[PDB]
Amino acid sequence: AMNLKREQEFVSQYHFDARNFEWENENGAPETKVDVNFQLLQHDQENQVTSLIVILSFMIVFDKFVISGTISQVNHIDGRIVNEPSELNQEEVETLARPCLNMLNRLTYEVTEIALDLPGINLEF
Amino acid sequence: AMNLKREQEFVSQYHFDARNFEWENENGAPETKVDVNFQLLQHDQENQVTSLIVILSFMIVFDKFVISGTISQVNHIDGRIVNEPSELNQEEVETLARPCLNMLNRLTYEVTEIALDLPGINLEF
């Protein structure tokens, strides 16, 4: 089990936009892309803690609309010095991103239910 | 009572953005502005119906974030030719905009509850 201390997850940007098919005719249709990246904040050598920001950025393309933005969370990994965030494995990355991914799922469910007047879309990320 | 036939309300854009105080230091803080405008679609002379689009555009500034976008609804005013939408009075304009305003209130309540982890903000528009 990762020994994580987590700060409050933070929405920097959450955008719902209807697709503009006139614009896409000229410029091409947007593509879905979802990415998790990491910013180092601090290595505490004495206590062996790495503080970083987990950053979830997304553009998710539906038939009629696009969901896009960035959600992030400061995480402290207790008991490990992670020099380069690329050394974290897939399971570690998912664990680190889990609160952000949940935020994305819950905003998307509520916004799509309300905006479309249909049962909410569950991304299940 | 207005004799309205309404089509489904439509979200063109609904954006939540954290304020960028570095950007605002250079560029000035955003200001709240909410506006209702009208696009004529058709005057049906025989049936005496004016079809228009009611367009609610908004930028709403909170301490830490901004809500902005556009929500619209095609309305048909049955029994009246409205040559120039500026001839509608305040009560008529509110009635025409009511579904859009409700959409704005409900998206804002849910998005703020989820994103901020606090009771939803009720705009009460």
Image: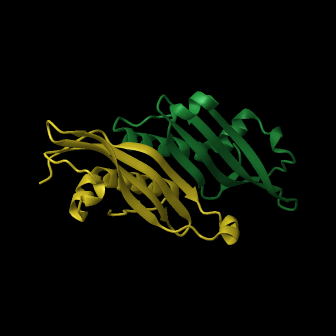
Chain colours: A green, B yellow
Give the residue drawn at x 51%, y 35%.
Answer: A19
Q: In x, y percent, where is residue B9?
A: 33, 43
Q: Tell me if A53 is positioned left or right of B65 in this view.
A: right
Give the residue drawn at x 53%, y 37%.
Answer: A66
Quadrant of the rendered structure where residue B6 is?
A: top left
Res. B105 in view? yes
Q: In x, y percent, where is residue B82?
A: 23, 50
Q: Tell me if A65 is positioned left or right of B44 in this view.
A: right
B4 and A69: which is toward the camera: B4
Vertical side of B121 occupied by A55: above or below:
above
B64 and B56: which is toward the camera: B56
Res. A125 in view? no
Q: In x, y percent, where is residue B22?
A: 70, 67
Q: In x, y percent, where is residue A16?
A: 50, 44
Give the residue drawn at x 40%, y 56%.
Answer: B109
**Quarter that holds the C terminus of chain A:** top right
